[PDB]
Image (cartoon, rainbow, N blue to C red):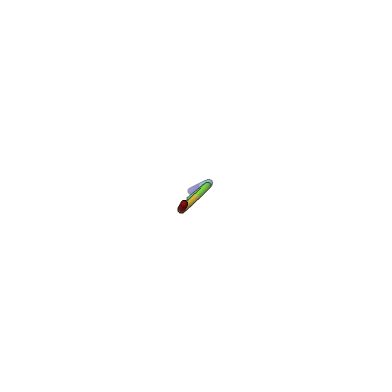
Length: 6
């Protein structure tokens, strides 16, 4: 599980 949020 990987979240990259901008």
